[PDB]
Image (cartoon, coloured by chain):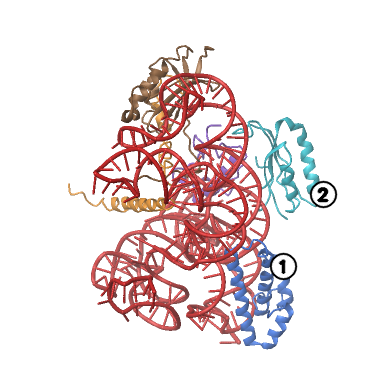
Chain colours: A purple, B blue, C orange, D cyan, E brown, F red
RNA sequence: GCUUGAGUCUCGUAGAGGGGGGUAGAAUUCCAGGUGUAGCGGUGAAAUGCGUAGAGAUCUGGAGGAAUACCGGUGGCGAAGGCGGCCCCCUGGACGAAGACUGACGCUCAGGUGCGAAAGCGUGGGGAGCAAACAGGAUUAGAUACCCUGGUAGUCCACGCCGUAAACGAUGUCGACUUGGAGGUUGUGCCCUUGAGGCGUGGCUUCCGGAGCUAACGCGUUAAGUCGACCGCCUGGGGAGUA
């Protein structure tokens, strides 16, 4: 696999929640980069987009909501 | 600290021109502004020991340049420490 | 985690989702903060993971059979 | 000056206050020599978890540029206001236009 | 009484014992049975068979309510937790959902020390 | 004088570097209420403990403290100690590309000065969970322990003190030189970004190995190789890091 964020020159922001729900699992946990194959730089800022979307209720913390 | 318009200001009065940014006279006056500004940061907070090592690095850097300037030209050394206010 | 599947009842399709990360987590929050043994165990782990990489790559020479 | 990326949710039962609340904030911003880059309101959308036993908050993005003491009066306005839940003052190097 | 139709069957699934209780959609309980009260005591409380007998003892005394469909909640890393649900669909129930609701702290309070 | 060491500046980049303030969710505990009934909890087994004054389980609401699942990585940053949710404010260093600038301003230091895990100490708070001491139940020949049920200082916050660790890479700092391979992480240049492509070039870092070195184990361009500068230190074991 590869990183589509490195395929372009875009920025992973928290407001683009359509592309973040394929990066979390079926219970709200973040999928590791050893499965997805993301670069380590973009994976670190991806989780910063997951954690900000969880604060603004665009993504759930757990599945019991 | 010591934003870009402030560094361009100090190099004008102490340097030969705006591109003489490395001389031993402009380096002492540039460190003195970074020393004097961070006293307001270390007036409060006081427990920032990881940042105080950066201040103590440039405090000891200014003494190693002032001791060099006294060794080279003593007339410029007495001119400089009066223009800033130094020697305790 | 949440199976509301139709047809014939057979959790079977439930233990696929649940035995994923629902028992390794609860058995390690079961006791002891550790605070430094995680480090030891963690560092023993990958010194034995590259023991599986650097031996099985060198095991493809022959097999004596 | 400084760029910011403010997003704050608003209590549903007060959604008719929202264009009043929006022009209340930007009048303080441009009255203090403040640039503005966006006003992209997202409307009432569904929450992921109940914020104070409540769903379907009203989201307001601003993404404005202001000095840091002018905006420091703005988040304490979000504190002492029951119609606002979960403000988020943020920041980028170059605030932008339409993103959602 | 109230003759409710759809319910929720919570399963507590500790290591030493399995508790199964049956409630409704609103969340207030109707009846319960444990593996320690089914005649199994001590070493046999931690058996999946003892969680089965606790289920059919709880599948009875809710005949008064008339449940034919229920959800299943499991909570705990127990030796039961799946042999209990096999004793419910065999008991004549329509299992709509099976849900894991075990408590996982996102790193909170300190657990006790590892016993030696 | 000179620019190669060292340093300044102009652009950027990564980061659990630090200090201050706010805030979120999960979970434990407690309190209150609803339902509900004889067990719960614990162990190799058991008892102490809890529960018919209604526990446990389950649901709603509330209070409070501490810690930040997944991401999390022989990953990153920091002089070391160390540093993980998120947001803002103040702030330190490292690094790269292309230049410009001062012109040896350097290196290392006895004494000195600062920083320095955890436990402890002082004053003032806070106190969920955990838990020395202590108390009970077991086990046992005995059990002053391991196990169990409780549980106080402490752990937390502010400001001081302490100045110690297997504070470890058991490897002082700095500089130069000497075959390679597989990676990780982070900048950047060129060519066909025409495709996650190819060629390079830096920084930090992990592993395996050559010469050589070492008593051997091993180390091996981040040396424990080959050298230079300075500092700390060693001189049989016990006594003793004690008087």
Residue at x 66% of width, y 74% of height: B21
- As helix, strand or loop, the secondary structure at mark 2 comes to loop
In the rendered image, residues at marks 1 and 2 fall on the same chain = no
Q: Is residue D56 left or right of residue C58?
A: right
Q: Disc 2 sits on a residue from what chain?
A: D
What number of labels is visible?
2
Q: Disc 1 sits on a residue from what chain?
A: B
Q: Position of residue F167 (x, y in %)?
A: 43, 65
Q: Which residue lies furthest to the left in this view?
A: C65
Q: Where is residue D61 in the image (x, y as percent from the top left)?
A: 69, 41
Q: Where is residue D36 in the image (x, y as percent from the top left)?
A: 75, 47
Q: How far apart are marks 1 and 2 (CA)?
A: 28 Å
Q: Quadrant of the N terminus of chain D?
A: bottom right
Q: Is residue E7 above or below residue B42?
A: above
C-beta proximity under 8 Å, tags 1 and 2: no
Q: Mark 1 points at which residue?
A: B6
Residue at x 67% of width, y 67% of height: B39
F50, D75: nearer the viewer: F50
Residue at x 60% of width, y 75% of height: B61
Q: Name the residue under label 2.
A: D31
Residue at x 43% of width, y 16% of height: E93
Q: In this view, does C31 lie above or below E65?
A: below
């Amino acid at each position: 696999f590869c990183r589509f964020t490195a395929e372009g020159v875009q920025e992973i922001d928290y407001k683009d929640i359509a592309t973040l729900k394929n990066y979390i699992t079926e219970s709200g946990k973040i999928v590791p980069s050893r499965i997805t194959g993301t670069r380590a730089k973009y994976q670190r800022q991806l989780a910063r987009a997951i954690k900000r979307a969880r604060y603004l209720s665009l993504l759930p913390y757990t599945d019991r909501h | 600290s010591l934003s870009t318009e402030a560094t361009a200001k100090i190099v004008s009065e102490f340097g030969r021109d705006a591109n003489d940014t490395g001389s031993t006279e402009v380096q002492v006056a540039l460190l003195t502004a970074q020393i004097n500004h961070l006293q307001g940061h270390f007036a409060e907070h006081k427990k920032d020991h990881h940042s105080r090592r950066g201040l103590l690095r440039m405090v000891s850097q200014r003494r190693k340049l002032l001791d060099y300037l006294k060794r080279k030209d003593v007339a410029r050394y007495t001119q400089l420490i009066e223009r800033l206010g130094l020697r305790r | 985690i949440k199976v509301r599947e139709n047809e014939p009842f057979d959790v079977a399709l439930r233990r696929f989702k649940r035995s994923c990360e629902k028992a390794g987590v609860l058995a390690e929050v079961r006791r002891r903060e550790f605070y430094e043994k995680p480090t030891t165990e963690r560092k023993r782990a990958k010194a034995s993971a590259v023991k599986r990489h650097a031996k099985k790559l060198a095991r493809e020479n022959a097999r004596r059979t | 000056m400084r760029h910011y990326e403010i997003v704050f949710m608003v209590h549903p039962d007060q959604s008719e206050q929202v264009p009043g609340m929006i022009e209340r904030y930007t009048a303080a911003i441009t009255g203090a020599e403040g640039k503005i880059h966006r006003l992209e309101d997202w409307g009432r959308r569904q929450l992921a978890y109940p914020i104070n036993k409540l769903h379907k908050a009203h989201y307001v993005l601003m993404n404005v540029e202001a000095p840091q003491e002018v905006i420091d009066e703005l988040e304490t306005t979000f504190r002492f206001n029951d119609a606002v839940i979960r403000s988020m003052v943020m920041r980028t190097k170059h605030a932008v236009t339409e993103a959602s | 009484r109230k003759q409710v139709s759809d319910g929720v069957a919570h399963i507590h699934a500790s290591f030493n014992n399995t508790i199964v209780t049956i409630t409704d959609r609103q969340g207030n309980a109707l009846g319960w049975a444990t593996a320690g009260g089914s005649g199994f005591r001590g070493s046999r409380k931690s058996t999946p068979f003892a969680a089965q007998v606790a289920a059919e003892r709880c599948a009875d005394a809710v005949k008064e309510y008339g449940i034919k469909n229920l959800e299943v909640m499991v909570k705990g890393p127990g030796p039961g937790r799946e042999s209990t649900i096999r004793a419910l669909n065999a008991a004549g129930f329509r299992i709509t959902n099976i849900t894991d609701v075990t408590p996982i702290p996102h790193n909170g309070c300190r657990p006790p020390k590892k016993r030696r």
